[PDB]
Image (cartoon, rainbow over all chains, first blue to last red; front, side, top):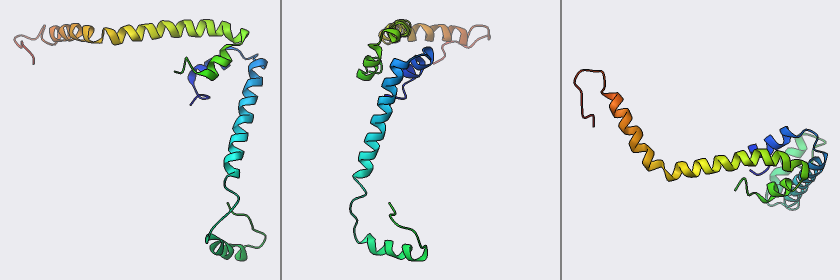
Length: 68
Length: 68
């Protein structure tokens, strides 16, 4: 909600030469990537009885693994 | 809240962003004052506009008064 505000878009359009603001924008994108990576890392750790079902689909398609 | 967003305030804290902030947020402050006055006078203006609409609703059609 914060990064998609119309005021932010208007400010970005008004000052194209915003390298100082561009640094903050890239910092925000890095925070985006870090948060998404952490959220996904909270997933690809463990599984359940779904492993037996998963083994059924790795046999018919050789060379396939790590379905998340 | 969008105007008072802490991230937007941090972006505001820039000098080159402050001039475009000057323009955009003086316009925004005028708009906020206008909308606050609109909320304050909403009841007052609705009765007056309703009276004008009723006057125009039955003005040039013969007969037809007291539309309720």
